[PDB]
Length: 113
Length: 115
Image (tube, rainbow over all chains, first blue to last red):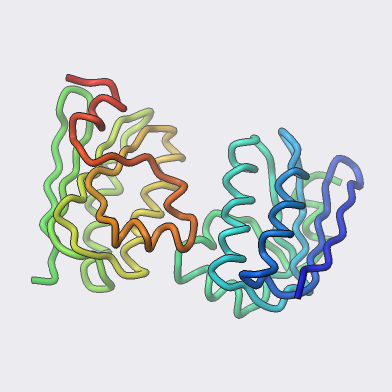
């Protein structure tokens, strides 16, 4: 259940990789881990290629993530949002806060490589 | 009917927008297209929602683009009179956390610094 997380920096770009399902039981541990890893004027990539589903509570984690990156003057890219997930974020209107692509490769060009 | 009654005005620097109805799939475009433009630059806007019963996904999405866009113009916004039932809905998601709200017009004008 818990989300297996991996966190690193390569050239001032923080890469948080997530594996699992943003449950409502599993959401808190990921939030606890991700928010402290945002950098001011910071560039982050959140790789969601192996996240299978978000419920309301997992989407709240992204928005949470987005609001403090927004306020930290930082830049965040989502990598590999599942079709299903995007379609669910498009309905609510949350999708339009975010920058997103399908590859780690394109994601680094967006932030400066 | 499904049409929302939307008044817009400016009191001493503040753009005040008043809504009557619910914001669903049918009623939302008109509210967004009407309200969204009056978002000026470095502005002040009270959105009075005292008389809105509810708002579907599409509706709250309207509050969303108003927030996003209110940002593009780096301006202010206070939501007045949001019901508990609508307020719970925006807490489910955490959208609620994007906004500044109060129950009275006075407090808004105050949060915006008026008389």
